[PDB]
Amino acid sequence: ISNEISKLDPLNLDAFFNQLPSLNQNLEVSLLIDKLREITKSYLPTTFSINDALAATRDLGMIMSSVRKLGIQPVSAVSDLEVFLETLSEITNMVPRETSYHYGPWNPIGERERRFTHFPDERGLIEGVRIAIPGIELAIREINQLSNLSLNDPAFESLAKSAALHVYQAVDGIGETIKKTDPYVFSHELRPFFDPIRIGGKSYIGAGGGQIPLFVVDVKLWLGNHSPNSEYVSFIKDSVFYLPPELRPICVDSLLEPSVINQKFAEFGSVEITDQVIKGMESLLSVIQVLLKFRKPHFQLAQRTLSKENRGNYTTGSAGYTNSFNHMVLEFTIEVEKQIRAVLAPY
Ligand code: HEM
Ligand SMILES: N[C@@H](Cc1c[nH]c2c(Cl)cccc12)C(=O)O
Ligand SMILES: [C-]#N
């Protein structure tokens, strides 16, 4: 529950986070490092509830990212963090780092909102994932119910429509980023806050909107187990254990099964094609077409951001890919649309 985590301040950092944008602007690394040290001596994380540990991962993660932004590995500089992070990670059963979950839906709205910088463009990122994630999560549950209904059942069409509506929340979220986040300001002022951090011998990437569980919708809906050695499966493979635990079984099951659309392609070309069946297959095109309404403007925005004019120090996103990856996911998604349009063409 997002609001039950967003309202917590387990490490009493509310005042500190009002100062953090200024601390970051003036490069006050000592104050950052003093705060990490104060936390490891002030708090016994083992006594935390789950929601407390999730909110503490949010707050501690963002301070660690500010230190890493300067170029210092924060756990190397504050070595007692490692034990602290290990204890939090056992309670959350999540990585010892913040993700888009902690930064968006679990990040409080209004005066307490945790932010790296004073730049209003940063709001574009936060609101983007804060809007996308709950809607994608609702679409995931509806799309998983589709495998067991008939294309001729009107409940199928109704569920698929409900999920297209819920996926639109991701469209609205990337639209908010496009309005609020200048590509140049992103590459020069925000991107450096999302770099990898070394914790207990492993490197954990920084938060990314690619951590919204849209890839989980893909796997269930069209990717399934049909593209084993693809670059997209390798990114999903790398993402499964960044997800909150409750989404991991859905994703793993889906990676090892035929997708909904491959199955409904088989059923369609094998059953009495009625008027409901065509409506049912048309509701899947509708979901796919909402994904395109997300991925097309998204591709454009990553292209402007990584252009020679607007990029700064980076040629890649926080997960380490170029816009070539985005293009590859978009082509995949366009191919699905073309395939469904063929199955429907004689109707
Ligand atoms: C200035 C803003 C943004 C830029 C420059 C950007 C760029 C990128 C890049 C470079 C990747 C490749 C993965 C990586 O290397 O990190 C990626 C993938 C992805 N990004 Fe963004 N992005 C931005 C905003 C957003 C927002 C606000 C969201 C969600 C609300 C989002 C959702 C995704 C998703 C879901 C993927 C996985 C690929 C896909 O599903 O098509 N991005 N993006
Ligand atoms: N990964 C992308 C943009 C990005 C980084 N962090 C984000 C967050 Cl926390 C939300 C939305 C987008 C982004 C890039 O590094 O170019
Ligand atoms: C993309 N974040």
Image (cartoon, grey):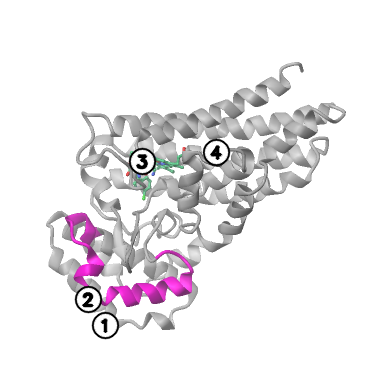
275 to the left or right of 319:
right
Q: Earlier in the sequence, mark 1 or mark 3?
A: 1
- Helix, strand or loop at label 4? It is helix
Q: Earlier in the sequence, mark 2 or mark 4?
A: 2
User: Could you tell me the amino acid type at mark 1?
Assistant: Lys
Q: CA distance from mark 2 to mark 4?
A: 43 Å
User: Could you tell me the amino acid type at mark 4?
Assistant: Tyr
| Span colored in magenta | 66-95
Q: Which residue is disc 2 drawn over? A: 37
Q: Quadrant of the C terminus?
A: top right
Assess mark 3: CB under 8 A from ligand 1? yes
Residue 41 - label: 1
Q: Which residue is disc 3 drawn over? A: 321
Density class for disc 4 (Cα within 10 Å; few <14, some 14-19, many ≥20) is many
Q: Earlier in the sequence, mark 3 or mark 4?
A: 4
- Helix, strand or loop at label 3? It is loop
- From the image, state whether disc 1 or disc 4 is nearer to you: 1
- Helix, strand or loop at label 2? It is helix
Q: Which residue is disc 4 drawn over? A: 168
User: Could you tell me the amino acid type at mark 2?
Assistant: Arg
